[PDB]
Structure formats: C-alpha cells, structure tokens
Image (cartoon, coloured by chain):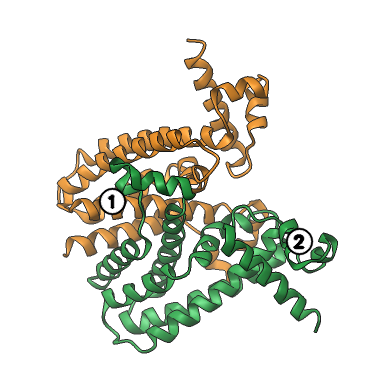
Chain colours: A orange, B green
Amino acid sequence: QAKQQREEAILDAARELGTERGIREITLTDIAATVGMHKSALLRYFETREQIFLKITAEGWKEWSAELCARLRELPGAAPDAVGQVFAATLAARPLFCDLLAQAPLNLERNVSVESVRSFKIATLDEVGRIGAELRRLLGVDETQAVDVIATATSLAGALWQMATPGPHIQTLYRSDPRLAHAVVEVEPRLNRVLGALLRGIADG
Amino acid sequence: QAKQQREEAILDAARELGTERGIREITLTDIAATVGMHKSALLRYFETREQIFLKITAEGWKEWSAELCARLRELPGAAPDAVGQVFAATLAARPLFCDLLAQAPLNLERNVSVESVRSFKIATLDEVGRIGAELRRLLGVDETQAVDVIATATSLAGALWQMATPGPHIQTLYRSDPRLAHAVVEVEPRLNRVLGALLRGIADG
C-alpha cells in the first residue's frame, strides 16, 4: 500500500502543519510542499484542503470518542459533575481537534463533495451515538438530551479554544490591560463549570 | 458628515452583502464594488474586511444587548427557564450576528490593529456586563456564572447557526438521508433546552 501510507503521510503533514501555525490558514500547496510531492499528485488523494481537514476532523472524533468512552466506562453511573469534568478535560486537552470542531460546519459547507459530507456526518454521528450511550447509562438521559450535551460540549470547546488563541500579540494585549481580563479565556475551567451545571440542570429534571 | 454617512453606508453594504450570501466569503473588493467607490478610498475608512466585520459585530452586540435587556428588564426575577427562553429567542432571531459571533475570534486574531481589537473587546465586554447585571438581578448569580452563561449562549448560538447553514445542497442532503436526521439543526429549540437546563443547574446551587 504505497497508497494507504501515502494518504496517512499526507494527513500527518496536514496535522503537524496545523500544530505548528494553526488551521485557519493552511493551504493545499503548503501541505504538498511539506510532503514533498507536486500539487497535482496530492489532488489525486484529496480534492481540496477542506476534504483533508474533514478527514482529520473525523479521525479526531474517533480518537476523542474512544478516549472519552474508555474513561466514562469506568465511572459511577450517577455523578453529573464528574461526567462534565471528563468531557472538559478530554476536550481541553485537544486544541487541534477543537479548532477543527469549530471550523467543520464551514469546511463541508460547499467545497467538499456531497458523498464526502455524507460519510463524514455518518462517521461523526456514530461517535455521538457511542458517547450518547454512556450518558444514558451513567445519567439516564434520553437521546435528545444526550445530543444536546455532546453538541454543547463540542461547540463550546471549539469556541473557547478560538477565544483562547487570538494571535500572539493579542494574547499579550489581553494580559496587559486590566479591562480585558474577561477576554482571557481558560478553556477547561469554563468548560467544566458549564457542562457540570448543564448536566445537573438536566439530572434535576 | 459625508464621513459619518460614508462609514454608515459602507457598513450597510457589508451587512446586506452578508445577508445575501453569508459572511465567510465576502471580500473587501465586493463591498467596495457594492458601495460604488474605489478600493483605495474604502481603505481610508477600513484597513481590512476583518475590521469592517469587527465593527458590524460590535454594532450587533449593542443591538442584541439592548434587545435582550429591554426584555429581561420586564421579567420576574427568579425563573431560569424563562430567562433561558429570552436568550434563545433573541439569538435565534439574529443569524448574521450569530455568524459574526462565531467568526469574531478568528477576525481579530491577526489582520486587525491592536487598538481596534482593544476597542472592540472593551465595547463587547460592556454589553456582557450590562447583560450580566440582569442575570444577577433576576437569578442572583455571581460575575463568573453570568459570564459563563453569556459566553455559552453566544458561542453556542454561533455554532448552531453554522451547523444549520451548511450550504443549499448539503441542507437538502441532510433532509434526504434518514441517517443524517441529527445533522439537521434547529437553533432556537436546542439553544432553549440547553440554556434553560444550564441556568437551572446553576440556580439549584
């Protein structure tokens, strides 16, 4: 498979490139330049940079879901704050995955084939179901509430991480002005308080 | 003031252009073309398209805050679900403002001057404080919880609206496949269930 390794190599290049300078500015050309192949050859594997990130976003969903479920699978089925804490810690520990969760709705939006979007959403929704099954078992919530929670966690983690990475000079700006104290975002803490309070509000119903 | 009207005219052109085809693809050139002036003249008013949207984002914060506070100002100080409902309805009714709330962390990120970011965050945080004061009065929450709530509402509304507007052909795709049912996002409903449950979980503490 100089084909399955080629694809896996292109993805790692995309990942490490995003780890170095973020994702909202990585080009298909840069990725090609990184893996050392012409853009035309790269295009045989991936139609656009959006399709590359959508596949990395999906790998991120699989990796995060497996991490989250392995941990929830060893928990006492009835502690809201404890479940929220596991969601907050796993997501807070995944900045690239969080950038991709925030960028996704925009990535599949129009420069990706219908069939790729279809596979992506199917793969994604399978993890939502997997994670949801643990929420049902641990806290006894219906399917709707489980989805609301997952959707909330992922969307909120994505937005908090964006707010936390405003650009080097802006981060320095936030810390320098006492009036911008609330602009400094700590992901895990806020995410924990929110998901805990959310899960309790649901459990007390 | 052919200067205050000029600026207000450029913004309306930017707004209506975003209303027509979205924001994640509007260029400084298109805006210039819309208002009928050369790009160089437009640049005298706004350095980049990010500075234009940041100013519209701020106007959006003022407009939304005033709407939200005028309504909360007539409420019975103690109903979590009712407060959540007002947040969900006002935000769900503002798709452009929601796209801008999701795009903001990325807009100020690096192509906007430090001083513009400083003014924007200050203006934004004043509304957070205004809205926060109503949360304190109606539900008796501390400053931290009030910010968590506002941050959650805005970040979640922004993400839900992006998920709800995946592109014409994708929206048709979501509705056509029974397996993608959960991919179809209804903003107000989810936002209401989440903010209500969140506020109760906080109030029950």
Res. B33 mark: 2
Residue found 75% across the figure and 65% down from its top: B46
Check the image and name the residue furthest to the top.
A1
Residue drawn at the location 47% of the way across and 16% of the way down? A4
Considering the numbered disc 1 on the image, is that residue within a helix, a strand or a loop?
Answer: helix
For the residue pair A121 and B134, the one nearer the viewer reads as A121
At 58% from the left edge and 61% from the top edge, which residue is drawn?
B20
Residue at point 55%, 27% (across, down): A46
* Picture coordinates of residue A115, whole percent (x, y): 43, 33
Q: What residue is shown with label 1?
A: A147
Q: Is residue A9 above or below residue A69?
A: above
In the rendered image, residue B57, in percent from the top left (x then y), is placed at 59, 68
Dot 2: element: helix
Q: Which residue sits furthest bottom?
A: B74
> How many other residues sit within 10 Å of disc 1, few (<14), some (14-19) or many (≥20)?
many
Mark yes or no: residue B76 visible: yes
Residue B99 sits above or below residue B171 on the image? below
